[PDB]
Amino acid sequence: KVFERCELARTLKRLGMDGYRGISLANWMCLAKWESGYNTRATNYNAGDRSTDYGIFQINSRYWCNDGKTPGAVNACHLSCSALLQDNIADAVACAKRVVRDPQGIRAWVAWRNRCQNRDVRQYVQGCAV
Ligand code: NA
Image 1 (cartoon, rainbow, N blue to C red):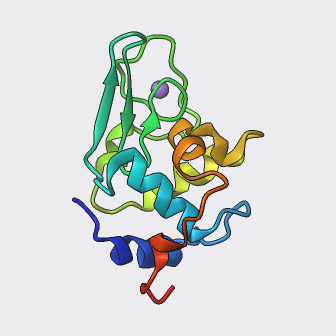
Image 2 (image 1 turned 90 degrees about the vertical axis):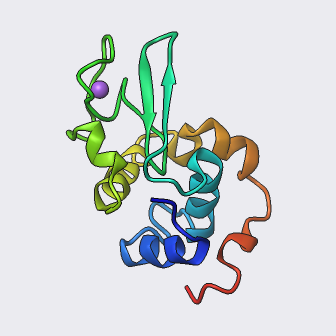
């Protein structure tokens, strides 16, 4: 599914993401926007290492989830990557929480560093009542 802006904002907030590891709701929104356009079914396959990024947060199969088809992969969130392509984003949020608990934090996502880090992102939650 493709979430509407404020719909996703409310959902992420309900799922405890606002301020998680010091990351504002607006930042999580900015990450989802640039990664998948709020599309839970988004997948990005990389032929170079045969890994695939899954879901709204575009979580990579070489390290975070298992898809049974990525060479030399690990599964840090202990979850199947298909659970990251569901309309119910509870699993995706839980795994995103895990990712950011590593040293680099939210800087793990190159898109976030390029389009969100140090920039105004207040627009993402404008008029959402969150
Ligand atoms: Na994996």
